[PDB]
Length: 80
Ligand SMILES: CC[C@H]1ON(C(=O)OC(C)C)[C@H]2CN(CCC(C)C)C(=O)[C@H](CCSC)N2C1=O
Image 1: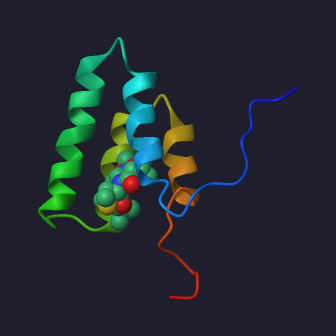
Image 2: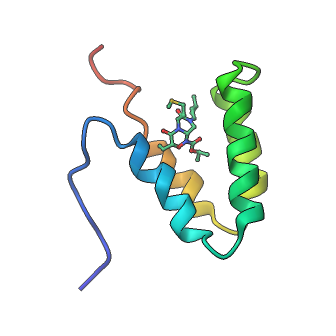
């Protein structure tokens, strides 16, 4: 039919995390850069709009990853 899976978990952070490794299994350079950008966020050097800017330049050939991440974010307009 179609490649779709509805119903995510409370913490889908680990899901997309490993997905990048499976997608770019033959391209370690792309995955390495992904980790570097994550480090900047871990150091609080960049914010939400900041990390997005980097992703938009790294995964320029894969907009799906950046777009899907918008919904793959637990923290949002939810009650909390
Ligand atoms: C969802 C899996 C995975 O995807 N992440 C990610 O950056 O995807 C983009 C590169 C497309 C990383 C980076 N961010 C960004 C935060 C910003 C405030 C939007 C995340 O929130 C946490 C990492 C920090 S919390 C552990 N994270 C994930 O959970």
